[PDB]
Image (cartoon, helix red, strand yellow):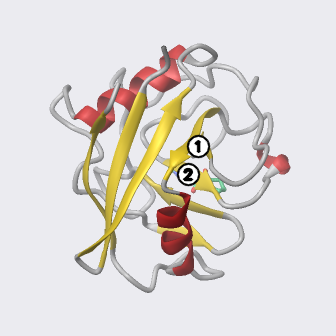
């Protein structure tokens, strides 16, 4: 079956809890594999210790820049960037997991979890999973965002990995 991965998140050094995500490897195997390996850190790099650097209430929580920690960086397990696999899955509502990018075919490691339906991102951002458990954790993260995306608390992925 599809991988189940986790993110344990702190806000200002205190645990918020765990976000569990299903990666739709059946639809986007290459995008799901990249995220799965960055969670385990099995390639010698990944999300562990990185932050949610851009959070916009009533929109989304963005993370994954483990190289520059500011939204300009990140890298995939394949190389610096990889193509848009497909746009089959849509940004249907809260809990959608999707790839951040800098235009077509620029997927790296940055991703976002939506807190609303974001239909304008369909056909532009590759959706590759959804929140199974921990939407309460996502709402907490979201509450520490702002209109500019600047976070009011330091949001850190302390631990991450694969459940199944
Ligand atoms: O912030 C985003 N892209 C900039 C970027 C991403 C990687 C490398 C360099 N520059 C980006 O796609 N955010 C998504 C979250 C909601 C709007 C779309």
Residue neighbourhood size for the residue with mark 2, other residues' Cα within 10 Å, grouped as few (<14), some (14–19), many (≥20): many
| Residue that appears at 55% across and 58% down | 135
Residue 35 image point, x, y percent: 41, 32
Residue 101 image point, x, y percent: 58, 43
Q: Mark 2 points at which residue?
A: 112
Please identify the residue farthest to the left as the structure is shown. 44
Up the image or down, 111 lies above or below 80; here it is below
Residue 145 image point, x, y percent: 54, 78
Residue 71 image point, x, y percent: 45, 59
Q: Name the residue under label 1.
A: 97
Give the distance between the C-alpha atoms of the residues marked 1 and 2, in whole angstroms. Answer: 6 Å
Asked if disc 2 is less than 8 Å from ligand 1, the answer is yes
Q: Is residue 115 visible to us here? A: yes
| Residue that appears at 78% across and 53% down | 118
Up the image or down, 71 lies above or below 31; here it is below
- Label 1 with label 2: CB-CB less than 8 Å: yes
Up the image or down, 119 lies above or below 42; here it is below
Residue neighbourhood size for the residue with mark 1, other residues' Cα within 10 Å, grouped as few (<14), some (14–19), many (≥20): many
Q: Quadrant of residue 8?
A: bottom left
Q: Which mark is residue 108?
A: none
Please identify the residue farthest to the bottom as the structure is shown. 152
Instruction: Return the disc, 1 or 2, that comes first in the chain's sequence.
Output: 1
- Horizontal arrangement in the rendering, residue 96 relative to residue 73 (left or right): right
Where disc 1 sits, the SS reads strand
| Residue that appears at 58% across and 43% down | 97
Please identify the residue farthest to the right as the structure is shown. 119
| Residue that appears at 48% across and 56% down | 134
Where disc 2 sits, the SS reads strand
């Amino acid at each position: 079956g599809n991988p189940l991965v986790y993110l344990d998140v702190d806000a200002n050094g205190k645990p918020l809890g765990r976000v569990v995500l299903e990666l739709k490897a059946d639809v986007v195997p290459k995008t799901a594999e990249n995220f799965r390996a960055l969670c385990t850190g099995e390639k010698g790099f990944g999300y562990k210790g990185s932050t949610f650097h851009r959070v916009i209430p009533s929109f989304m929580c963005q993370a994954g820049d483990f190289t520059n920690h500011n939204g300009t960086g990140g890298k995939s397990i394949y190389g610096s960037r990889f193509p848009d696999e497909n746009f089959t899955l849509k940004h249907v509502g809260p809990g959608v997991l999707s790839m951040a990018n800098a235009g077509p075919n620029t997927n790296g490691s940055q991703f976002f979890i939506c807190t609303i339906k974001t239909d304008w991102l369909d056909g532009k951002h590759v959706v590759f999973g959804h929140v199974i458990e921990g939407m309460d954790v996502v709402k907490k993260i979201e509450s520490f965002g702002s209109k500019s995306g600047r976070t009011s608390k330091k949001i850190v992925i302390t631990d991450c990995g694969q459940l199944s």
